[PDB]
Amino acid sequence: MSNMEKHLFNLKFAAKELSRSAKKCDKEEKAEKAKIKKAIQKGNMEVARIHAENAIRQKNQAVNFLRMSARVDAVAARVQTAVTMGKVTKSMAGVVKSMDATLKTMNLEKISALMDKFEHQFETLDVQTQQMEDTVSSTTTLTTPQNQVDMLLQEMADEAGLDLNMELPQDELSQRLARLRDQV
Amino acid sequence: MSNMEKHLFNLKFAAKELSRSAKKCDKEEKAEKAKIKKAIQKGNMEVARIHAENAIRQKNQAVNFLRMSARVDAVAARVQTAVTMGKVTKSMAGVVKSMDATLKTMNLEKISALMDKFEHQFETLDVQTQQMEDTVSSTTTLTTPQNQVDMLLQEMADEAGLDLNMELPQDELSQRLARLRDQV
Amino acid sequence: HAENAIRQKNQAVNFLRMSARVDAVAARVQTAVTMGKVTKSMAGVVKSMD
Amino acid sequence: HAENAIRQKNQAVNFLRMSARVDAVAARVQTAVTMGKVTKSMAGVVKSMD
């Protein structure tokens, strides 16, 4: 509970306290009006005037409590805007300072370098897996003869109705630009 | 909970707090409008004006809370992009450094060697299993006479309708290239 | 609300595209994790057969 | 999504092909594990009969 949060709490409460006072005054206007009727019936005109004065007083008091409640509510609304924007300003100031740190220890030139390296290292890993696969391929070469694989593909293609020959080997812009590179 | 995660949490919460404030203001516009009607019916025009002023205030306050919620949400979205890309950058920097290590202790020349060796060693194992099998074959030679195996194969082929003779022994490009190697 | 709707729309395309990028990276790191394991096991087979 | 779909397609062909390679190796290491056991047992039979 901050200092301004404590004040906000107190102001919100004062506004409710005033609103309750206006309700109590409205309830007692009704109760005093009921007593004027009873006094008029009994011909007690002095007691009737005492209740009439109470009823008019309670009426007018309620309008005052109600209006001050409106005022204290407006203030409390404004103090809420100050409490929240103060919190947001503090959090932004914190984001600004933590990013000022991080962007120093990892500036753009250093990211440039890290990214370049990441790229180049995965190129070496691709070179590495190719030569592992090539080695397994030759190690197990007699377990997969070329001609047997080609014939199984042809059989499976014929059964599928695919018009292709599997023993044989199987853009224009690139060819145009190649010809330009020759012609220059 | 990182420093920026703490800030993100606070900003996401401030945005919700503001959104709730706009809902409360909308609810109280409706409640104050209801009181204007009751006051007009009773001819309390001073109380009617107090509620009218509250209703218009609560209306306009809600638009302010709503708009500030939108702003704080936008900020929190951006801080989320910073929190996540900071995590990704850290993980990439870690991948880059661990691969820098591994590619040193197992460079391409050393993989070259390991693969060559793997290949050559399984060639010796193939030489070894051939000579084990040859030895078992001769050890048990009188339990499998050639002529008996040939006759059983012929019997099984005849029963299957296969037109083949089992006692007798059973590409063009290779023969062409062989002839080229002779002719040169 | 119109400004929020257009903001949330455009934010989602950004989150989605960065997810695609981080996924691609993670796919590549999976190829490095597995081929590292295979390379270690082959190196072990090579030495035990030696 | 089109870029993700084409990436996931092409990644699967790579995973599948490397699985084939690692399987082939594992088949060969199985031949070495078993013939090593047989060679040991024969060497034992030879020495007990001697």
Image (spheres, coloured by chain):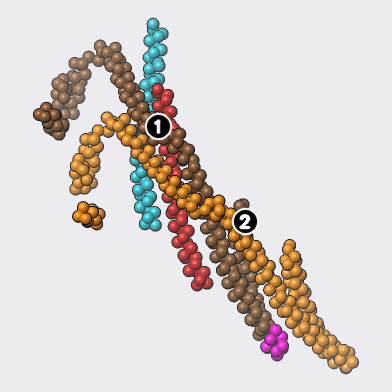
Chain colours: A orange, B brown, C red, D cyan
For label 1, the residue is B110
Give the image quarter of residue B141.
top left
Residue B56 lies in magenta, yes or no? no
Residue D4: percent from left, percent from top: 39, 54
In the image: residue A66, left or right of residue A108 = right
Q: Looking at the picture, which amino acid does disc 1 mark?
A: Lys
Coordinates of residue A164 in the picture (x, y in percent): 20, 46
| Residue B145 numbered mark, or none | none
First in sequence: mark 1 or mark 2? Answer: 2
Tag 1's secondary structure? helix
Residue A98: percent from the left, percent from the top?
60, 56
Look at mark 2 in the image and give the residue it sits on. B6
Task: Residue at 63% x, 81% y: name it.
Answer: B56
Looking at the picture, tell me which residue is in the foreground, B161 or B76.
B76
The chain under label 1 reads B
Q: Kindly tell me whether residue B36 is visible in this rendering.
A: yes
Identify the subunit bearing mark 2: B
Marks 1/2: CA–CA distance: 48 Å
Report the number of discs: 2
Residue at screen point 73% across, 72% down: A12
Residue B182 figure quarter? top left
Q: Determine the residue located farthest toward the top in the rendered image.
A: D50
Percent x, y for residue A135?
Answer: 33, 33
Q: Residue at x 38, y 43 (%)?
A: A123
Residue D15 seen in the figure: no
Local packing at callout 1 (Cα closer than 10 Å; few below 14, some 14-19, many 20+) is few
| Span highlighted in magenta in the image | B39-50
Disc 2, SS: helix
- Please, what is the dominant secondary structure of the magenta stretch? helix
What residue do we see at 16% from left, 29% from top?
B162
User: Which amino acid, by three-letter code, is at mark 2?
Assistant: Lys
For discs 1 and 2, the disc positioned in front in the rendered view: 1
